[PDB]
Image 1 (cartoon, one colour):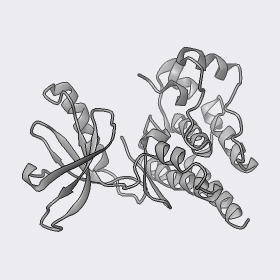
Image 2: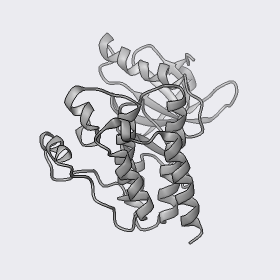
Image 3: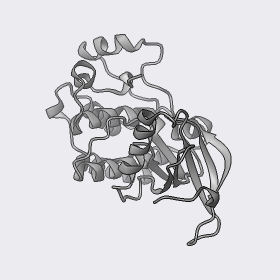
Length: 255
């Protein structure tokens, strides 16, 4: 998986990332003389502590093979350290939704939620807990294809047991997925706008939940509310979410 630097032509900055900016580029590779790629960069990669955390992402991504999870291409492990990934040419999901807010039909938003459920059902099948499911970590490969893209605390996405006890499980992933579904149906608006991170848990324990997005089908909003059961053991699993989303999507396409 090591790629010689000379094989990479660093292009335009596409977006921000957790450890540094992400660029598009070209990988002049034996298998393909001009492969379009994404290049993740890492500021402070001279710190062994940061460089280790950054490169853990590569190791994690390499374990997975799913149509809606971005693929690792390779790594450059000399400074400046880079991760070379599959390029999703339409970029970050939040920006995509905001920009195409009045061009994307309801069926598209539901499709994106369903596709993400397929990736998350796959991760569940491997007993892998993600811990940071949110629209910011989803990328857009085509108008009909999103991919999970990334492997201080995101309090406004987190399940109550994660905020209170730093417990992260398959069940807490489902709570976060419910929030991500809300975000999609809100065309990339953040949850709990105007609320301080410290006040979120109080509202959750008081039984408050994100309201039904405009134009959201009632079946879909109800699925979100199931994800937001206070008791983790009452939350659905991703097999059930996938199934229900598939039915909602088909219903919507039949309108």
